Image 1 (cartoon, rainbow, N blue to C red):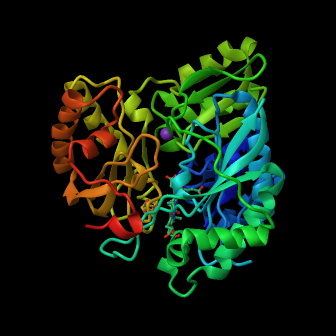
Image 2: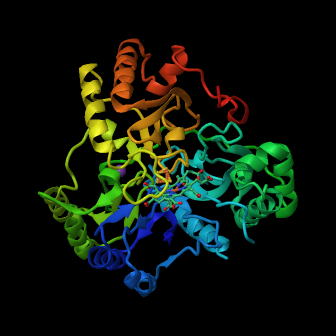
Length: 464
Ligand code: SRM
Ligand code: SF4
Ligand SMILES: [K+]
């Protein structure tokens, strides 16, 4: 298992050229796959090239996690904050936390984020430990801590569940690393290590109580949490296209379907990004939506970058729906896949696009995700509409998450095929288009209209 460490998704152009060369010359599939934890993956590395890949990473200052005994995963950071000035400091903290957590064997893998409101692109409620940035005058002052998210479930096993993360309170910036260590060590000591399916922090928190866990974190960190400082999210999508950054700089976010970077007929996505890497003055940022930001472009350089991106297919226009849809890798490389996800999503969203147009809502979107099995890598258990693989061509259909990702969708129909899913969604999108209140999301609508009951307390009410 290769898990390349890349805190906050920030990768230099020199690093990009090295991984582009390795992908093209030394793997079966020839691709760079952007992951939804803001890093990248190679597929099909032969025996001959396992030592070459660690040497390649080392040659450009990169390393991979030693997953055999390191339970941490890549630390996420909001990639393109609306207050652009905040990114540098939030990224420095994501790096500091990532380095602090490098090898305490944990009972189960442990996932961390740094989040900049109002964007929940990094999907904080899928993660064990979340630092929500609070700023004054463009400078970080501290974080709200949320603990205990995680999405993996087992079909037919009501002792497993997806759980969102719980607020603990606010900490000043100076206590960040002491708090991070206290959460990690409390989970290390209190986790149910014997039953692997019950070892995640989400289960520990439910077993001992949020207040009990919080009190122990306070004791170990040597602090008292302050009350939560106000924060609100407005969405989880990327900002596709150009946005103004700091100074005279601009950020170009490229939609990349499934994060799969390969040269396709009339669409040389991989060569295009190499050509951009060779001229770009700044870094790239891999987003938690499996897209890529060409970050820190001077205004004078926008036209040159955009020319390559447009000619290579990297700026091919897609619907808002497609920009807000996601799938996990699944087949052909994942050994755990029950149904296709990545290879299913493009034509599935073709069909969803037709339904949206039919009902007059082609400018709207529904956060819609497909995961190939209930481990949940595609983050379907935080979607407005989630599909969870069950068997070849068959999925459980979940409804009633929200746009900002703070609610788990309940299962609506079990073990159904794509035609059955599209027939259900045709009827329901039609109802939404005609009956929604101003700005009301599809997920919230299915709850308000009584189509599905909400999940209010997942450890107790996720399962019917
Ligand atoms: C690539 C990625 C999906 C994607 O399309 O982007 C992915 C792919 C895989 N995940 Fe994951 N996971 C990916 C994000 C996630 C997330 C979402 C997230 O973290 O934001 C989850 C759900 C959140 C959570 O952990 O609760 C996730 C939960 C899992 C689990 C279930 C863990 C559990 O608690 O039970 C497994 C299975 C396991 O660990 O045994 C897993 C296992 C796998 C493996 C390695 C399958 C395996 O054990 O052999 C997958 C490799 C497929 C392949 O061929 O490449 N992956 N995986 C993501 C890589 C992120 C990264 O860079 O580290
Ligand atoms: S959700 Fe299942 S099928 Fe998809 S990548 Fe994760 S483990 Fe593989
Ligand atoms: K994408």
